[PDB]
Length: 203
Length: 203
Image (cartoon, rainbow over all chains, first blue to last red; front, side):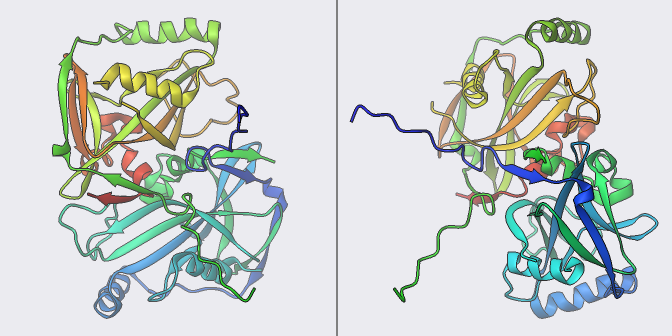
């Protein structure tokens, strides 16, 4: 002995490096329109109620795809209305694996591809059949109506996306989302905070 | 061959489990008062300016210690005034390792202990010699005046803390912090979001 051990790379929990690529490295093609399953707010919560009694808590997963321009991180979002933006993702089927399910949904929505999903970035819970969502399970709330899990999806150097005709694929800079719950909601507007721990490499 | 490999535990990047313990498992004793280095806001930014020219960007580290009550996560904070709360932490010395530095600061402030610091939970940047802080580096900001890094510090089943007499050690539930920037500031109020990805075990 008397030898010294070469140090191991820092734990990924301590320092998580993510490679980002130029916005111009990505392109999109069109595909048939994808319509929302729920016509209105009323029908949305009505279906949420009906399904809760059959399969229980709704399990939603959403993917956060990051790119950059001028070394500034941008999150890819789907624009469906003047001020209506959403992350690619959706509802899991009963008993379906969270990551496998997100991969299925990513493909259904943006598939032209082997999605790399190795990071959980957050969780949000809906206690009642109402709009309110929280980043924790509220006190005495033993039966949340919905659980949304966010994952960071690592993109390859270049990629081609297929986007439903009624959707517009945009890249939103973090400064556009930060403290902008009125424009993007509580989840998307807190993405800057959720992504701050990452050590991004601007390729 | 023809054999099958037993699956490895899920990546810590995908699922990070953290053990939490009852609030009653922790106690505190008093120690001499610890006074703020800067008397006022004016002196604070004046010192920030002076030091920036000597050693460059200020590097601050803060520890987030979590406990629970009734299975509800609580963050330990130091109360210094009616509505003045802070996380244990402080300024690193030039060339000092981030984690070793946080351990030094945790000991100076709460030391009765081997702090377990294996997780980075966020980063905040101060672009100018003003109060504004952001969870990302603003565009064209190549010379931030301060960089604050937040780490999750895992507590043992039981622990004794020594708290400066002029401080009050409190456990703040997440619902008290969420969307309460007016009461806790932009960093502490976003801790619920930053901690949502963790799979907490309520022992």
